[PDB]
Image: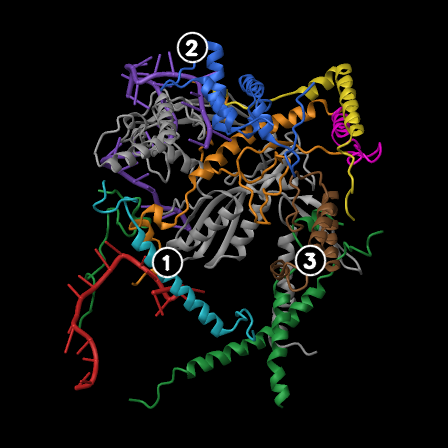
Chain colours: A brown, B cyan, C orange, D yellow, E blue, H green, J purple, K red
Amino acid sequence: AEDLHKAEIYTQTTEKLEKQWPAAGGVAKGIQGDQFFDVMAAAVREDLQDQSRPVLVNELTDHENPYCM
Amino acid sequence: TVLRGHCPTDKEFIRRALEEEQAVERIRKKLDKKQLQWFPGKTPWAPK
Amino acid sequence: MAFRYRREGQFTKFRVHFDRSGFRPYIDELKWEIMDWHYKRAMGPQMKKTLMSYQEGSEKLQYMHDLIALGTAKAKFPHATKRFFFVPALPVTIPYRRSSNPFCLLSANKTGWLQWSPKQRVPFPQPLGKRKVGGTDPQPPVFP
Amino acid sequence: GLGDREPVQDTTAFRKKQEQSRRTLQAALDHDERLARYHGAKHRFFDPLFRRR
Amino acid sequence: YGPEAPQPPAGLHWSWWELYVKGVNPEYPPRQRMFAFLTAQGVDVLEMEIREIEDVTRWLEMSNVYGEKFPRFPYDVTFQDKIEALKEKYPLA
Amino acid sequence: FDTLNRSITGFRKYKAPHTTAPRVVRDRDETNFHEMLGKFRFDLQGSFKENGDMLRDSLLQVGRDLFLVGWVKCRSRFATGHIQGDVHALSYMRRYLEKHVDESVSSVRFYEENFGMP
Amino acid sequence: MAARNPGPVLNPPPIAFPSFNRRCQKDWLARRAFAENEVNGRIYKNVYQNLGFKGPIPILNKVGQYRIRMRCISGGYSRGIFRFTRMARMGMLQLAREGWLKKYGYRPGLFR
Amino acid sequence: PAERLHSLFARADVLAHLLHSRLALPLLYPLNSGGALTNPLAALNSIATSRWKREEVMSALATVTPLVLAATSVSRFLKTAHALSYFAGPACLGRSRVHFLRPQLWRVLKPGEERTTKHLKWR
Amino acid sequence: VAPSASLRNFKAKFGRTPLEALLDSEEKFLTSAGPVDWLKDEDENGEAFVSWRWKRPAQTVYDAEKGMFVREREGVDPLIKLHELRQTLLSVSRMMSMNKQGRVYYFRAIVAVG
RNA sequence: UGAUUGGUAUUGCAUGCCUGGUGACUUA
RNA sequence: AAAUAUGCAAUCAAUA
């Protein structure tokens, strides 16, 4: 139950990060344009998600995808 | 777009994409058939 | 052409080389899968028995190892009245390739270990009838 | 939030604490014999044919 | 007691490669001897392939348990030449 | 009639070296009553087409999905069978035979029901 | 035959763990020797073709691709072996009947 | 009216979606032969009531039935249109057998119908 | 709202609506599933399933001393109380028959019951 | 590019698995 | 007829 709760918390955190640091024009278009602000925002969001990703007890696979977790 | 479950892109765009795909498929088939060999690396009259 | 979809596979089956038909083999995967099955079936229960043998110093050893590795050891034991359950696991032996597929279930693994479950209602290598999977009964036979 | 700007996991103090924890674990293993086996237990894998024979 | 914990190379929580190379898991005294000998010679064993590691292990075991005349290689090749080639290919850091 | 009916022949057939009957687990509650096994026999009378091939295929598919075991026998006007498996699977099979058969089923009968088999 | 004294029903041998077979071991040795010496044979052939001479290469007799045979992986027999299976008749039969091929599209209900 | 006819089929599609949503579940939903009876979820009556009434679902299905019966009028109209689309216009001894006088009986394995002749001998 | 003629006829000939009968059958199937049968208690709020009872196999009788069920055999007169009869095996023999493939063995038994 | 715990010696009249030939497979 | 200069299989129009 605690692992499921942590997974739900992680999904909520990912949604909050997506709303807080949206990538204008789409991820692919931002990558192709290669603007400093877009790169900074994407890196910040990715690092925050990496930091917030939990460590569950019953699974030894630290899935970075909230869907998979 | 109006009908549910149908592709929303332009029909002419789809036609152009399909024609390009068919042309590239024909080119690929021609090239593969020409370059195919049972004993790869063998050229006629070369020292065998 | 009275039965098209019935004969759909005939062309590849009969009049095409394997190297050019596009058919994808299975040997290079089942070879590792069978050994994985045998290794798991042999080692999992023994691992669980070894884990549950003492059953009193498990938390103490976990605490000491957490102190040695992380230096905090409060991730699993915030206070004295918190219980950390140990899930049996075995080394992963089949060299699966890490892939960019975000939905891959064995690409984000970083520990080199996988959780093992003794319970599986559906037997995976379902034999035909009375046949038993080889290597299942090690007891010597008895003759009349 | 972000992580540690200057993590201390690469510090001599951390290394000394790790050594102290290792010494404590070794002392506990020496003191307790059941714990010693429960920690040093090893299990090798052998062929099912070899098991049969 | 107990085996020393593995050192993750980068972005990992474990490494079976180091344990295998050192012959700790699976435990194999011949592989431990191979690792020690290559480390003393100055060969980065972790950078070697499985084939080369097994070949060196077999050669060392044969030399130890049959004599210095063995192993014997054709074309006047020598175990010293093999070791020199391995050292040149994988300098020890 | 049953697929396990055999007559004793004149040549020795290997017998079980020992005899050990697994015990019947009688301490079953709501948390464990789903792990019990069972068996029953069924007889259907009516009209079926293709000499019962359609019903045979349907029953085989249902049994393959439900992991049931045993045997079935379908013909033009009748069907019989002996089914074994988990209690829930047996109940599903009974419901299917009673209500979910695409042939004329004038009569259905269930008999020789047993539960709690090891 | 109607055996007079039938024996117990024996559990079949493991699929992935064949018994010792020195012939299979030597086949593996030949495979690895060919893998190691493949480049040298190419160099031999390049030199001979450049010099315009059809000379033999004796070492290929020992370290060539043609010293390798398709031997059953699970049985060790060196005949009736297909690349799509790498196993002989009985190895294939045991693998199929144990249920290891259902995942890989095997259709036991198909004759042709 | 024009707008009424414009919105008629959209509103009919809304009705059809409602019917589909209702029919996409078992009749006695959420009743079940498992957790429903073996693992019930008093102080918690506000979030989960063990009590349950069938009249609600019965009335829902009773109201659903006539709506689908009416929707069958769509099928009737489509069939009428299909039949009309194939209209033509103004109006303009012994047995015969092919492929044997009678079908042949086989006592040997037929290469085609092996699924029915497998039990028979191959020679 | 006036019921339709078909519904009225169905009620007259069965006493329940078609939906009522269908849902009664479905509820009975869902409740009498597995090895047990659940009991329903009805009040103002609604129905609930709080108790279950073991299902009794058809045409079987529970023996107290054995603690298990035993089947009821046809041909026997059900009026006779089998718990006050006893039996003795006088003789059992291995008879033989001959068929195309060889010899077939069956058994004969003589038993006294009183 | 990840090798291995002897015998293709007798005994198919010790057997398992797997095949050939002949017989069968009827219900409500 | 200032159109053509004409033999057929065992795959593919959900794409030649």
Disc 1 crowd rating (10 Å Cα; few below 14, some 14-19, many 20+) is few
Amino acid type at image mark 1: Arg
Disc 2 crowd rating (10 Å Cα; few below 14, some 14-19, many 20+) is few
Residue position for label 1: B28
Amino acid type at image mark 2: Lys
Residue C57 location (% of width, % of height): 75, 24
Amino acid type at image mark 3: Phe
Q: Residue at x 56, y 53 (%)?
A: F95
How far apart in space, not on screen, are marks 1 and 2 (Cα)?
59 Å
Q: Are marks 1 and 2 on the same chain?
A: no
How far apart in space, not on screen, are marks 2 and 3 (Cα)?
66 Å
Residue H8 location (% of width, % of height): 61, 82
Vertical arrangement, residue G99 with respect to residue B24, above or below: above
Q: Which mark is residue A36?
A: 3
Residue position for label 2: E69
Q: Chain of mark 1?
A: B
